């Protein structure tokens, strides 16, 4: 045989490159996944991740209450935190024994897979009683925030999209939904009559994941890295795997 | 300048009237919210509210178990209430230490925003095992109950729609879903191929809210009133804000 | 991160203090002023910062 | 340049030696720290360390009760140990359910920094009700125990001073204070009128540290060694760092 890495007859090398390119390209096909992650960052350094993975379109929607820190199998101040919610829903509405709940998120990162069309991204960032813009009567039910998403890059390849906003003020009390549509450069509408019931089935087939990690390090090590997910850490360092035309 | 409230040159007055009219009219546009509330009334005087706010269409769906009273951070008889559910799902199926669970709702009020089309309203009022009409085989999955909705009015303006039914009998054991479609007097179908993926995204963008209030007074004071929501109290008194062509 | 950890310290003296006498020992978590005892001045005169 | 370690022009080498000598010599200046450690050894192998670090003079004073083992966040027999204290303060004064409290120290090691003057060391080893010598009326409030202190040595340099006494008998029930003065070979009295208010301020500026370590190994590894402290372990092995005229 020819010697490795010296000719066009390195079939091992050609198949390795095709195997990675096929994964990149299958994800961006209408057969492929589109994925979203919401990361809620707590003052104790822990991170709630909510992930959803589906065909055609994907989204996450969470109440104010649902985004607050919950430590499985430890004390949570569950009675005082009910009182906190009453004081967040209406000023002086509660009888809590604290000024600021440490269960409140300090920040949100939203990440989309590279199979999203950025121009389709929509966010409903609500007040604590799940109203997008002060009152329902004057509320557009979403904002198109695609222009704010940064490219997560590894080796010059887009491996995901990140929108990050801090909640460092006492009045940063939010409900949150986000939504993106899978890339479709074709003129076959996946929602046309031919395929619309497949899109309805995708709503039931979407897989959800939720976990609280103790630290960003543990998130990078045991969640982002093993699953080849894209990520952007507090030091602006990019994680993910470049696949397109790569060994 | 002209004197206030004496001529057509009161621009402050004209802009105030337009500001309110624009809110009324934006809500009823296809860009606007349609909202539903389910109120579950308990014997202890507390009220569970479930709210959902979305574009194009909106709904709530709850199991028998999910509508039962839950007091965050207090004792709930959690083991005996598992036993109650077994005796509700099948006669003599449980080993509870009580005849009647006080966690069972005594009544339900369903309220829709004034941006709903009443003729689109649909309700699935199920038995305790989530079957609409005795057996699945003979079940229509919904009833069109729009004719039963009363107009919530303030100053002669429709500010919402109310359907109220009591559950005062031992055999009133229910699961519950309700659904309404946003007003669309146009011949642009929001579900046509052009916009259907926007309707799929609205399913992910819908914002949910859920809270147990200790009393109707607290609900009116700290939930209905501050958010300019419509409401109908046990004394048949109407709440909401009239906006159309009003200062 | 323990939420019990202080996020800030304010030190206030009455107006009867002489500011030039003020001394602070801001130690590490094992109560050593400056990295090791051997090289530690037991205080800093921080009056100029008040 | 000259080659490393072959001439008097190794300035790297000369600065390394000066850096260590300056630390040794600064500690022994009147600007420097004088430090004391009390180690209380428990039957379960754990060790309470109390450290104090101050200018000019330093001391520790602890009640019988304060030297007993306390396990943060575990059960301590807190009611029965109140009863033990009553039976220690006066024979048959208590109603404890045990002959010997395992919270009682089995031994004490007192260590001073090498900046102490050994001839200034004073100890008040009291009975369980904090009386130095049987009755207050006949009590000298201290003993000058300097002659009993062993030199902790590394590489022929004194890195600290150790006095160790076991408490292996049932009647070994003690309160304890110890005190040493910083080296002052000069005839400038740090307590003269010129500097006495600086010595008063040193009383407020003194830094205290207290922790229970699970084992002598953990004490050597995570307390003694990282802080360059002197120590003498149960096997008579010396710890510390020699600094004087050393690289
Ligand atoms: Cl395709
Ligand atoms: Cl419109
Ligand atoms: Cl000096």
Image (cartoon, coloured by chain):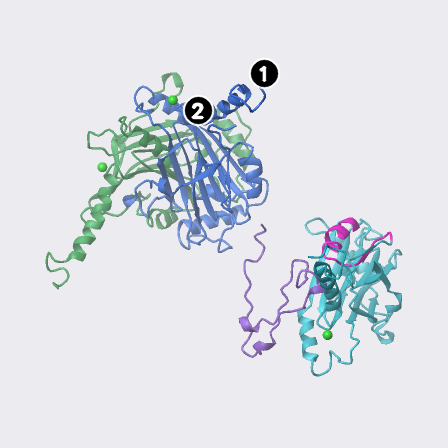
Chain colours: A blue, B green, C purple, D cyan
Task: Answer few, some or many: residues within 10 Å of disc 2's Cα (few below 14, many 20 plus, some between 14 and 19).
Answer: some
Residue at horizontal 54 percent and vertical 66 percent from the top: C10
Chain bearing mark 2: A
Callout 1 and callout 2 share a chain: yes
Q: Which chain carries label 1?
A: A
As helix, strand or loop, the secondary structure at mark 1 comes to loop
- Residue D38 colored magenta? no
Mark sitting on residue A26: 2
Instruction: Name the quadrant where ligand 2 sits.
Output: top left
Nearer the observer: mark 1 or 2; the answer is 1
Tell me the quadrant of the picture where the N terminus of chain D can be found: bottom right
Dot 1 corresponds to which residue? Answer: A1
Tell me the quarter of the picture where residue A123 sits: top left
| Residue at the spot 58% in from the left edge and 50% down from the top edge | C1
- Position of D219 with respect to B9 (left or right) is right
Measured in 3D between alpha carbons, the distance from the residue under mark 1 to the one under mark 2, in whole angstroms, is 32 Å
**Residue nearer the viewer, A35 or D26:** D26
């Amino acid at each position: 045989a020819d010697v490795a890495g010296t000719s066009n007859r390195d079939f091992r090398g050609r198949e390795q490159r095709l195997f990675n390119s096929e994964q990149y390209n299958y994800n961006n096909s209408l057969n492929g996944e589109v994925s979203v992650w919401v990361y809620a960052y707590y003052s104790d350094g822990s991170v709630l991740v909510i992930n959803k993975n589906s065909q055609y379109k994907v989204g996450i929607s969470e109440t104010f209450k649902a985004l607050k820190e919950y430590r499985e199998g430890q004390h949570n101040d569950s009675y005082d935190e009910y009182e906190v919610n009453q004081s967040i829903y209406y000023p002086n509405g509660g009888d809590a024994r604290k000024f600021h709940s440490n269960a409140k998120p300090r920040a949100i990162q939203i990440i989309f897979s590279p199979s999203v069309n950025v121009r389709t991204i929509k966010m409903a960032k609500g007040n604590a009683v799940s109203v997008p813009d002060e009152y329902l009567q004057r509320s557009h039910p979403w904002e198109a925030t695609g222009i704010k998403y940064r490219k997560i890059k590894r080796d010059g390849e887009i491996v995901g999209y990140s929108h990050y906003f801090e909640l460092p003020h006492e009045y940063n009390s939010i409900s949150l939904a986000v939504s993106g549509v899978h890339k479709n450069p074709s003129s076959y509408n996946v929602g046309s009559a031919h395929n619309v019931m497949d899109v309805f089935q995708s709503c039931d087939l979407a897989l959800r994941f939720c976990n609280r990690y103790w630290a960003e390090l543990e998130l990078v090590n045991h969640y982002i890295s093993p699953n080849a997910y894209p990520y952007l850490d507090i030091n602006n360092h990019s994680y993910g795997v470049a696949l397109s035309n790569r060994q």
